[PDB]
Amino acid sequence: KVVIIGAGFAGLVAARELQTAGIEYEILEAKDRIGGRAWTEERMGRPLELGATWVHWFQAHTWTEIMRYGQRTEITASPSGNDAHWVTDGKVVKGTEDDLDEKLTAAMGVTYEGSEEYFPNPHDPLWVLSDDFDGPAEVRERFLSDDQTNAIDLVKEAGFDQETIDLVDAFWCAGYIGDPYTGSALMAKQWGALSDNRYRVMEDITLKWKLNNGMRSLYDGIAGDLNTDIRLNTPVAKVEHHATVTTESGEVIEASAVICTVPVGALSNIEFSPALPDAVQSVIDDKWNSQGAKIWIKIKGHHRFLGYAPKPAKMSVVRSEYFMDDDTTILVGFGYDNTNIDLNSIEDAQAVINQWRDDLEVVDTTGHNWVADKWAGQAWGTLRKGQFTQGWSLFDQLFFAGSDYAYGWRGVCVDGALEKGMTTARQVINSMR
Ligand SMILES: Cc1cc2nc3c(=O)[nH]c(=O)nc-3n(C[C@H](O)[C@H](O)[C@H](O)COP(=O)(O)OP(=O)(O)OC[C@H]3O[C@@H](n4cnc5c(N)ncnc54)[C@H](O)[C@@H]3O)c2cc1C
Ligand SMILES: NCCc1ccc(O)c(O)c1
């Protein structure tokens, strides 16, 4: 009676929540698998996360699922103390990881600089624009101005030198999963607000703890709780919200309400009748700022490596992640432009490593191009200029659920999908009561 489109974390958790409340549901999943943009799979000799990877106990929704499905102790920190390399003026600079972090810490201090006035409650991101806002006019003006400013311009304008600029440029190529110069700096400021405004905490939350048993231990857990079979290989083609849903084969399914978790980068596969609001339609057409890609590279030997490179490098942040039995290292990498790298080309993977070193030898590589993926069309959702205040909040019988619309760790984190999936089901629940 309630139709959930997509079996990623938002869809699975919404179904479990409806089930709790005794409401009939059905999940229609385009792919032949569950997990969506979280995808644990054996590649290159071990389970690797092709999408979502890191977790933290300060992420409320993720951490309760970690507790629920038995992974409390089953988390491991990514290697630290790497030999660090960063490109800053056509040149490769060699340092320690702590050397890099302290440069990034001071720049982050400036980047967060008004989060305390914007986000007293870091989970009320649009409070400044609320009728309830009790602050001065000049804070609302700085807020809107920040939505139209990118995060690197904030560091440039504070007088930092070119070294620190290319470091933040590389950082946000990875963080904004695409071109950071088109991004909204209010995203970065809210990550600060959710991280006690400390670079170190922000990295502990987003870039440290991995699930020993992968994301699949969680989404297999949620799916294992459901008493209604997920209909895989059932891509949705049309949605009528007056609700009626039409699959690609032409099957028609009737429903009291529709919870659509299809990411924006993939909504163009579905026709809506009536059409979507013009405001929301312009977001879909502009979509999100996530055009980048994530790679897994394997090299010869055991090397503790960290590398940073600004736009337009193939990869902006690359880091050792696993030391393997056969004297190899698996590194992870994040880059701003999915179309500048073939994630499964040993030669393109070598050119990534060649950004910093001419003595490290790639022997394998792999990745999934989420942006080119029909059912995704993006990496993790990040914000263009103007999308903090006129973007993710515009998607509020038809409900949109997904990390990209979350109040808290929006887009970038499974925490956001688990948040928004659950609260969107509550909207359904509340209105049926
Ligand atoms: C490279 C990468 C790395 C990430 N790393 C992390 C990390 O370390 N930590 C973290 O917390 N988060 C991370 N994330 C983010 C996390 O994966 C997402 O925020 C979360 O999985 C989004 O869940 P969702 O349910 O909102 O969307 P999705 O996972 O995209 O779920 C949508 C589902 O709908 C399906 N679908 C699409 N179109 C249709 C259609 N027409 N009909 C039917 N079904 C359809 C899709 O197949 C998919 O199963 C990462 C994301 C990426 C891309
Ligand atoms: N994949 C985790 C998302 C992410 C990307 C870049 C960062 O700089 C960061 O702190 C977190």
Image (cartoon, grey):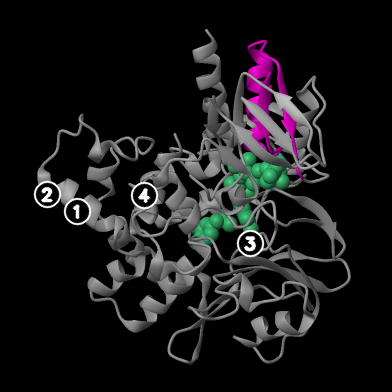
Specify which label sits upstream in the sequence, 3 or 2.
2
Confirm whether residue 64 shows in the render.
yes
Q: Is mark 1 within 8 Å of ligand 2?
A: no
Which residue is disc 3 drawn over? 371
- Where is residue 184? Give x, y as percent: 36, 59
Which residue is disc 4 drawn over? 388
Front disc: 2 or 4: 4
Which residue is disc 1 drawn over? 142
Q: Are marks 2 and 1 in contact (CB under 8 Å)?
A: yes
Q: Is mark 4 within 8 Å of ligand 1?
A: no
- Where is residue 288? Give x, y as percent: 49, 56
Which residue is disc 2 drawn over? 138
Specify which label sits upstream in the sequence, 4 or 1.
1
Q: Nearer the viewer, residue 7 or 224?
A: 7
Could you give the CA–CA distance between mark 3 and mark 2, rounded to whole angstroms?
Answer: 38 Å
- Which amino acid type corresponds to the residue marked 3 in the rendered image? Val
